[PDB]
């Protein structure tokens, strides 16, 4: 076991930084404690290359604070495929598939990261993903909207999703809120409402259906709220995973978007500007 001593201020900041990391959701309190003890802090300077495309993987990072740009060099040209804003994680691909870094991550401000060495990672996270794969691989392959992906790409979706459970009445997401997750209902029922004024029910999602994609596609705040009816289980994915893996089905989703407009105009007379 690898262990790094941390001040009290570090443990509080570390625990708060890890609370929403999807790759840690399917871990028991004991595996999680080992991960926490293995975490070490790392300061980064603005302009610093935390990760360079092509290198061997070494650590997995959870963001404590700071901004970062994501670059993928495609044919001598560097594209900015996204960014991180004071929250999130990265560097898990090289450690899961033993491949070279697939992108360059640069800090665009001073910041801090929580690192986790590859050994502790593969020993716990990777071991845990195998378990996750046995529970959901079948379910994910069967989703109609994911048929657009190559079969190998679909299997990779399982590696980065995390399970989230909600009790009856819990708010899953709120209208007007910023968005960082894409959801897939695993079990239970999710009620979608929108405020004209009072809240109006506009849709319900059952096993196999998704929601929370509109904000990620149009880059806007959540257009509606979502609450759980009874006990709900959702498979969540962060926006970076969404953009890396679901590009192939940005059509089927774009096609479902148009429907959102018609429905709202029909119910309210205005499209509420969701596009
Ligand atoms: N579109 C993307 N392609 C590849 N890596 C990405 C992308 N968006 C974010 N990343 C992250 O950037 C990291 C770069 O190193 P890794 O390949 O280990 O893991 C990668 C992911 O965690
Ligand atoms: N008519 C609709 N307009 C907007 N969002 C809708 C509608 N029907 C269902 N939704 C879903 O509710 C989600 C609310 O958050 P998002 O905007 O991220 O994504 C939205 C869609 O997935």
Image (cartoon, helix red, strand yellow):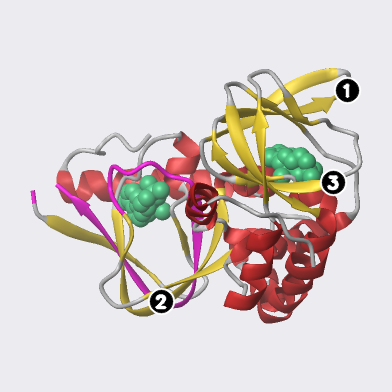
Q: Please tell me the numbered disc located at residue 58.
A: 3
Image coords of residue 182 (percent x, y):
51, 54
Q: What residue is drawn where x is 67% and y is 80%?
A: 135
Q: SS for tag 2?
A: strand
Say few, some or many: other residues with alpha carbon within 10 Å of mark 1 (under 14 / 14 to 19 / 20 or more): few
Q: Nearer the viewer, residue 73 or 49?
A: 49
Image coords of residue 49 (percent x, y):
75, 25
Does residue 103 appear in this view? yes
Q: Quadrant of the C terminus?
A: top left
Say few, some or many: other residues with alpha carbon within 10 Å of mark 3 (under 14 / 14 to 19 / 20 or more): some
Q: What residue is drawn where x is 84% and y is 32%?
A: 53
Magenta part of the protein: which range?
174-197
Does residue 161 appear in this view? no
Give the vertical position of 249 relative to 46 (above or below): below
Q: SS for tag 3?
A: loop
Image coords of residue 171 (percent x, y):
30, 63
Q: Nearer the viewer, mark 3 or mark 1?
A: 3
Write down the residue under mark 1: 75
Write down the residue under mark 2: 232
Spatial CA distance of label 2 from label 1 is: 44 Å
Q: What residue is drawn where x is 66% and y is 61%?
A: 37
Q: Is residue 207 magenta?
A: no
Q: Quadrant of the N terminus?
A: bottom right
Q: Nearer the viewer, residue 157 or 46?
A: 46
Q: What residue is drawn where x is 70% and y is 70%?
A: 141
């Amino acid at each position: 076991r690898i262990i790094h001593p941390k001040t009290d201020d570090q443990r509080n900041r570390l625990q708060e930084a890890c609370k929403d990391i999807l790759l840690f959701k399917n871990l028991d309190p004991e595996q999680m404690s080992q991960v926490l003890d293995a975490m070490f802090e790392k300061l980064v300077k603005e302009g610093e290359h935390v990760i360079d495309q092509g290198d061997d993987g070494d650590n997995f990072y959870v963001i404590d604070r700071g901004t970062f740009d994501i670059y993928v060099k495609c044919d001598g040209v560097g594209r900015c495929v996204g960014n991180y804003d004071n929250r999130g994680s990265f560097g898990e691909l090289a450690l899961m598939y033993n491949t070279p870094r697939a992108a360059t991550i640069t800090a665009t401000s001073p910041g801090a990261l929580w690192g986790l060495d590859r050994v502790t990672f593969r020993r716990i996270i990777v071991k845990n993903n195998a378990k996750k794969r046995k529970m959901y691989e079948s379910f994910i392959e069967s989703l109609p909207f994911l048929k657009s992906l190559e079969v190998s790409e679909r299997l990779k979706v399982v590696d980065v999703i995390g399970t989230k459970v909600y009790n009856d009445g819990e708010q899953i997401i709120a209208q007007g809120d910023s968005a960082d997750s894409f959801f897939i209902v695993e079990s239970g029922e999710v009620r979608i409402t929108m405020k004209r004024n009072g809240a109006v029910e506009i849709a319900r999602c059952l096993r196999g259906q998704y929601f929370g994609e509109l904000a990620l596609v149009t880059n806007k705040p959540r257009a509606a709220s979502a609450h759980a009816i009874g006990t709900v289980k959702c498979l969540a994915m962060d926006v970076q995973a969404f953009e890396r893996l679901l590009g192939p089905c940005m059509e089927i989703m774009k096609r479902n978007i148009a429907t959102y407009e018609e429905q709202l105009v029909a119910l309210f007379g205005t499209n509420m500007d969701i596009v």
